[PDB]
Amino acid sequence: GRATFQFLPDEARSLPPPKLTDPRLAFVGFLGYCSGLIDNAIRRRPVLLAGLHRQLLYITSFVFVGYYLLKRQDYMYAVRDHDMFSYIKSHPEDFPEKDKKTYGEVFEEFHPV
Amino acid sequence: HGSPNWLKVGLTLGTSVFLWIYLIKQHNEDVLEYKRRN
Amino acid sequence: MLKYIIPTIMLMPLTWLSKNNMIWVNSTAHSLLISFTSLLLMNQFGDNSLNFSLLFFSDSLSTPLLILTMWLLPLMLMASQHHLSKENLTRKKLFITMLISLQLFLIMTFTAMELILFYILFEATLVPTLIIITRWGNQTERLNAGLYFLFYTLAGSLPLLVALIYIQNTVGSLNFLMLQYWVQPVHNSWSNVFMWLACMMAFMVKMPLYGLHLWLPKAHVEAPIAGSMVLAAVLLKLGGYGMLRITLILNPMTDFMAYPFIMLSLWGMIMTSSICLRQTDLKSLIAYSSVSHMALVIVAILIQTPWSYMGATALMIAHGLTSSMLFCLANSNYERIHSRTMILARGLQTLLPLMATWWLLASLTNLALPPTINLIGELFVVMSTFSWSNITIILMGVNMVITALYSLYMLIMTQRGKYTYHINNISPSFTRENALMSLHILPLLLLTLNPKIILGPL
Amino acid sequence: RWIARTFFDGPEKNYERTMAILQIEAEKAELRLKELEVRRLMRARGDGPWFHYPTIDKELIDHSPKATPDN
Amino acid sequence: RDHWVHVLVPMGFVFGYYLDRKNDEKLTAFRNKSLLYKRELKPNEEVTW
Amino acid sequence: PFFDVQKRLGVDLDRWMTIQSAEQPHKIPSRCHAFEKEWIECAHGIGSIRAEK
Amino acid sequence: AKTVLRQYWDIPEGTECHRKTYATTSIGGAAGLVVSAYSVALKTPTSFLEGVARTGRYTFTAAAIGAIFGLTSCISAQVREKPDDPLNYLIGGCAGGLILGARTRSYGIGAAACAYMGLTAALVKMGQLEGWQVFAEP
Amino acid sequence: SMVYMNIMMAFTVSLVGLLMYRSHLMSSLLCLEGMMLSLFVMAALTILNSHFTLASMMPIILLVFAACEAALGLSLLVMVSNTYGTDYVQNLNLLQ
Amino acid sequence: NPIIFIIILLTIMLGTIIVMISSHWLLVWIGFEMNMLAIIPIMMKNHNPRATEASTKYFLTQSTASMLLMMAVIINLMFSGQWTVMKLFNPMASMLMTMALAMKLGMAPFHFWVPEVTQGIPLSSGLILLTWQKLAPMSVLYQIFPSINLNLILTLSVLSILIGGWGGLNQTQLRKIMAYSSIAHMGWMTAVLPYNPTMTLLNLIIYIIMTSTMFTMFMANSTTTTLSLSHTWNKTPIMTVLILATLLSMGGLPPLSGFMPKWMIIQEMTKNNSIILPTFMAITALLNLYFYMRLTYSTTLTMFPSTNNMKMKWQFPLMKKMTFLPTMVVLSTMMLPLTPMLSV
């Protein structure tokens, strides 16, 4: 949690990175693929297959940004579990070892209809 | 005939190739930066 | 579902992608082809159990219920074309796409693998239904009925989220129904009443009790083009089945307070069918039949211990096919006489002889003539709640009495004559009018041969 | 005979698939009881850097012999 | 033309069935079970995974 | 939200005029200068939730 | 303040039926002042001795409710079977609400004042009966 | 000491009934500029005995905005009288 | 006039940065002092005698709401003399703090700051600029957060949606219908702020997006609900389908992404054994939906396009950043497993 005011810090090197052909990155920009079609539909285009140069660079936008956004999402869970397991590792008095007991110990309710 | 403005038509075609090649070089580096660190 | 959702979304960029009036034949062609694939991997075996792929499917293993959900988009397009063909193609492409968009979420529903995946898909509907209610109706009392359809379904379903998120961080996680092996019991307290009650009451608002049925003859009375979402809204009512997924486990030992849900829904059963014999609107006549012998399942679920789940499952798709066709009998014979008043349509049975069989074999399934899927359903419910208390044969027997006099009152109003009027009503029930009236009884009496396919676990 | 092996499987796939996606859950539903053990109840210690509130930085203090003999 | 509007769209079945197989080839945890379900000695419970 | 730009790049926008014992332009302290420096010494790496008690 | 509840919820518990309704008319009596103060401020100026807000009967109403609101309970707490119960304290709902039903005439207000007040009556003592806590912390 | 109670009693020159009411709105903008010197003094008594040596630039800067603030507010109060001739706070047209 | 309109507009967001970039209560005083100095010209531009009689009702409400803040500083100047932005060391200060700042964000008390300004400013164009003043004090309650009384911050927030809800069913003027349900969406976020003060910002970033895209849709002609009828069959029928989608999204229905906050925000409100608190508010925002239904019953059902006037010409306004707003304000509910790990 240290090294304040970074977009993503230096210590995110040992994370996988989240490489492509993941369905979110297909979906990020699929809505942008839908968004460029709206961009024609607002203005009485009347094409719905209009100028491709407006219909491109929406795809380029979301995918690049969404990739560069997801590198810290996988970092923040990785730094989340990293600090929990240390506090699990110290203080064993807050984390006891439960006893293993099979179904020869329990006498449950017993409620039949 | 066709009559666009012919100025920005291609800037959209030139920004992506700038963006994608900057992306893939950032990706093909960082694909090795895992093993270079781990 | 591996990919049943993945072809049925591919139906959607086919309709607008098409040409002119070919848009009717292109959609109905491919939509029938899923009915092989729907059957194909499903109906497998079978002894504890079929977890299907992942966090997206438990395959709807012991309750099939889903093949019937896939008939309908190639059943409603042939039904809706009667009075729709005066609007623009730009809106005719819309009304096919939201109808497919209603089938998309129902497919991931009924399977759903979880209880929190269920709710967000349990509530993922009611937006594409409401568009079919408000636009595309007839004259007014659409708009208040568009609001009575909300605010019962949505007022009840929000205390699910308070209780389902409460379970997710109390005992492990609810994410699987097969991590429900560890279940602590739920005793008698003053907080465990409300945990039972809030988790249950949002299902009562769709499959109605005698109280809070006040939205059901509102949306069905004032209704789209030819029953076009009314066929969907009868599946959606029985698509609130998830009480079978919840209450079998997950507070299993609260029958202590079942009694205000029993007596309200067992005496209401004998009255809410009795309150319909003086109806004058024909589509509101059927709309109260759908109240009565749907509410027989509510005293069949809360009473546990199968020989009821034998029948309570068979009753969900008993009138899934019956009450669909009765709406189709009334979505027809309104194109010719422009009123739904049951007085006016007399002088019949001479003019349209071929559809006399379609009236009777509909109304012979409420009399229910034991070798059908109907009196294999009721006679397991009857032999179940007999073993609760013996006195329940009385009310449920008079239920069998009045609906005999009720179903024939809709038949016998057409056996009269001399017609007095009506230079119109010429059309002799064309090839489409019998085709979409068929494919209802053709699977309905077929499955009576080996109805082991229609059974719970059980 | 030519329906089963032509289309689907038997009790060697859909058995021990339920052994496989029920060992993705016993390491999911046991950690959600340990977040709520530590996050919600840290508590009076503030030990791990979740509930860590800033106070003041003692780097900016001064140690020069400031001209008052009794400060 | 060649009508990609038509039957090319039900060809998304095998396209969907391709993605249907990719899960069970990483859901390969247990060859160790006791209810036939064996994977004891044989090349029977290894195959079709 | 507290962006804290002035910790990244080392300018002091303010900071100096914040506490009772910081700079003192010609080194004339306050009346309680001895207790400021002593009390800030207490809670530095402490996360202030255990410092109250 | 909260200590009024620490003399309400602490000592009587059904018995001592005078101090029960002496303290439980203080709270409901005090809230008549709060509805009086906005009815002279958010409403425009009344007659010569403000607060003289338009229809009056405000603090005339509110303290009368809390006057009976222990009294309907503490009578019926001991006379039946001697606990305090959710069905015990339910009784103070309806006729406790019917003060607002008695004035500003009924047949459309009074039974609706009876019904809904009986819903919110029993849940309060049910609250500590299960240990409910509205404004909590981890 | 008592030099703080008076003046903390004198901070109640807001008192909100007389912070926008009644009419002749100049009477209300009066106590908005007169609510200062109950902050300019109440700061100055605290920085000065306890020799902070640096925070006493803050009472100088406390006037500089509140003068520029109230000068802006006085510009608009001409505009209510430029359209009428009388300020009269019981002018109200745009409901709520 | 054109260049000086930027320099006024530029310093509005420069006023709010110093609110966030500060370790010192004097600078957060200057920060949203000059915002109250640099909004007053934007109220004026076309000089109509309601606007002059509206900004002056705007003005002194944010002069006192300024002035009590400096009173709250000088109290805990006396107590321990530290001026870092942190806990305030005095319950007589923090009480005077929170319900001073509740006027700038206006809560349910301190009432009519919100309708009486936003109604009838002839600049209905924007007045999207009333999203900065909801953004500056929220950046102050992120730090003050572990010093409050926990009753006042809820009682201003339980009253928030109960009275921001009822207030607008009695309306036609769609600026007031946007002015209302802007107290309600300040009710959901400060009911949560004592419990895990992040997953508050999730509600705010959603609230900037869905409200900014509502005003841009409104900038064709739209003034009143009866005028919201007469553009389906005249201007563009695709506008009617779009204006349906955002409202049904902003009501919180789970097929869209205005259900994204609540779904997550109850994951925090219970988990803290507080159950009767969300069940009140979750059922309260239900009649916050009867604004939107009965608004969608105007435009989407062809309700009387009379008075035949043809717009045979195209439209050339500037719908800036509009093509990407109802593609992240509707379709994002699947694509946010962790938005609350970027913002955290």
Image (tube, rainbow, N blue to C red):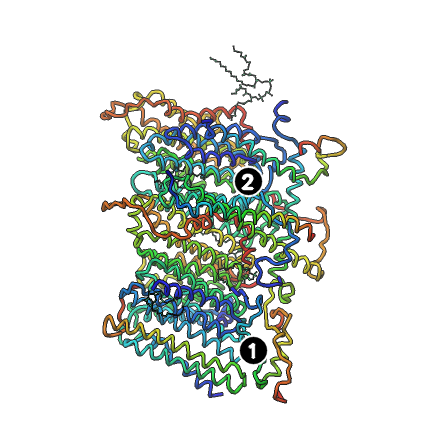
Circle 1 Cα neighbour tier, 10 Å, few/some/many (<14 / 14–19 / ≥20): many
Whether residue C458 appears in this view of the structure is no
Q: Quadrant of the C terminus of chain G?
A: bottom right
Q: Are marks 1 and 2 on the same chain?
A: no
| Image location of residue I123, percent across then percent down | 32, 60
- Displayed quadrant of residue A92: bottom right
Above or below, comparing residue C399 to residue C356 in the picture:
below
Whether residue C173 appears in this view of the structure is yes
Nearest to the eye among marks 1 and 2: give it. 1
Q: Does dot 2 land on a helix, a strand or a loop?
A: loop
Q: Which residue sits furthest bottom?
A: D69
Circle 1: residue type: Ile
Q: Which residue is mark 1?
A: F19
Q: Which residue sits furthest right?
A: E41
| Frontmost residue, G6 versus A61 | A61
| Frontmost residue, C42 versus C412 | C42
Above or below, comparing residue C216 to residue C423 in the picture:
below
| Frontmost residue, C444 versus H61 | H61
| Image location of residue F8, percent across then percent down | 58, 66
Circle 2 Cα neighbour tier, 10 Å, few/some/many (<14 / 14–19 / ≥20): some
* Subunit under mark 1: F
- Displayed quadrant of residue G65: bottom left
* Subunit under mark 2: C
Circle 2: residue type: Gln
| Frontmost residue, C104 versus A21 | A21
Above or below, comparing residue G76 to residue H58 in the picture:
above
Q: Which residue is mark 2?
A: C304
| Image location of residue D14, percent across then percent down | 64, 35
| Image location of residue C8, percent across then percent down | 49, 34
Residue I315, disc: none
Spatial CA span between label 1 and label 2:
72 Å
